[PDB]
Amino acid sequence: MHLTYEIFGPPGTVADISYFDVNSEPQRVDGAVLPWSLHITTNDAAVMGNIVAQGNSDSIGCRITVDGKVRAERVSNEVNAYTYCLVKSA
């Protein structure tokens, strides 16, 4: 019953990670080379969190695994997750 989130990316990539902590304490890192993982303990039920990334990476997505069973997972593919909003047009 442990909720753990983790991101991936190339070696030397710098991205700002922001997420809402259960105890009320957002985490933000600047000047990081690669993403890591976190450990969150919850009562005893399905839990999920919202995490996003905005770095000059080629692939950025999120993932959530609970009770070792798949319940909810969101994967977004982006060749440059740093445009905030730019759909091919030019």
Image: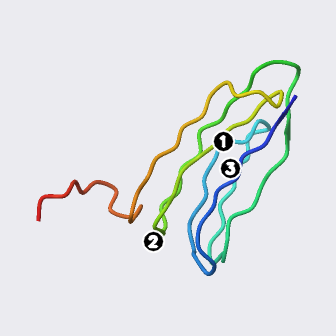
Front position in the image: 68 or 4: 68
3D distance between C-alphas at marks 2 and 3: 22 Å
Query: Label 3 near label 2: C-beta < 8 Å?
Result: no
3D distance between C-alphas at marks 1 and 3: 5 Å
Q: Residue at x 66, y 67 (%)?
A: 29
Q: Residue at x 51, y 57 (%)?
A: 60
Name the kind of residue labelled 2 in the image.
Answer: Asn
The residue that disc 3 covers is 26
Query: Label 3 near label 1: C-beta < 8 Å?
Result: yes
Q: Residue at x 74, y 35 (%)?
A: 65
Residue lying at the far front in this picture: please name it: 69
The residue that disc 1 covers is 20
The residue that disc 2 covers is 56
Q: Residue at x 88, y 19 (%)?
A: 44
Split into 4 quadrants, where in the image is the C terminus? bottom left
Q: Is residue 76 above or below residue 14?
A: above
Instruction: Tell me residue 82's x, y (percent).
Output: 39, 64
Mark sitting earlier along the chain (2/3): 3
Determine which quarter of the picture holds residue 2. Answer: top right
Mark sitting earlier along the chain (1/3): 1
Residue 78 lies left or right of residue 37; in this view the side is: left
Instruction: Tell me residue 80's x, y (percent).
Output: 39, 65
Name the kind of residue labelled 3 in the image.
Answer: Pro
Q: How is the image coloured?
A: rainbow
Q: Residues within 10 Å of mark 2 (few under 14, many from 20)?
A: some
